[PDB]
Length: 352
Ligand SMILES: CC(C)=CCC/C(C)=C/CC/C(C)=C/Cc1cc(C(=O)O)cc(O)c1O
Ligand SMILES: [Cl-]
Ligand SMILES: [Cl-]
Ligand SMILES: [Cl-]
Ligand code: NA
Ligand code: NA
Image (cartoon, rainbow, N blue to C red):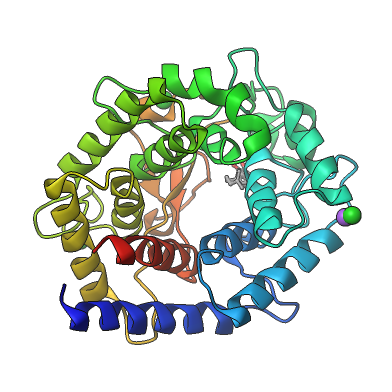
């Protein structure tokens, strides 16, 4: 054990926590992502996710920040369903609501009236195939005011999503109901593929974690195949290479590192985690952030199969007329990515 590397993990985590606490807005929200001149900037979703990521820290001042985040989420009580959404002006969605319920658990509020109401609302998003859909059709059509989408199918946006199903399965009340859907959606290579995310490491880590938390021996082969996939994804240099980041995605690497925590016996897995930690420590910026790489994609509303859509472009790189559909946006504040990385390092440190 190299005590310098453990001490650098302390210093790295601390610098990231400082960045994240200072990055909150006037009311105290974490904000990230932007749909310019339209849905604008995420707050409820980003705050629920960042708060959940930070729940792994033992620090009293971090717990205080999470208690404040929950108070802010409870003030967002304007939707008749009790759900949360991307930000104030969006309708409710199952993904935001699921992350908000994970944050509620971290602050002892799983049994609160609001949490009970929001969990009940999640049940409306369950699909006949046993997964969770992000949106109710009536709610998201009401929000969207784009003429050429008026009479189009929303069955893509309102279908079962593996990414959101995996996140909701982190909630004990839903884990058993979503089990079979998560099992049957695993690919032949051992990974899962998500709807709103480019990086399969996110959906794969969350799904394997939900199967692990259920404790069923029947699920351990699936978990092990996912870990084997993660080991393949991680380069010897310590990063997951992507088309966009061929020398390593900080977001994909952090999620892969979380996936690899699910096997604590295999020496190759242990060495891969050590490599990923070293690379992440080297990539940290002086302000304690990591480079933004949380790539959120917007399929057409009618598209059930975004992993079969070869036309993705980065919204911020498109010249001239552009639309959100078929484009990828990112966490311009680096809050989403940094929270992800810092969580992965806190969880992985003790397994060095
Ligand atoms: C927490 C979740 C589920 C994140 C996934 C991304 C997501 C769907 C954000 C919600 C905001 C939204 C509808 C962005 C797309 C859009 C907006 C408009 C508009 O605001 O006018 C128009 C579009 O055509 C469009 O695709
Ligand atoms: Cl209550
Ligand atoms: Cl790169
Ligand atoms: Cl797909
Ligand atoms: Na309440
Ligand atoms: Na509409």
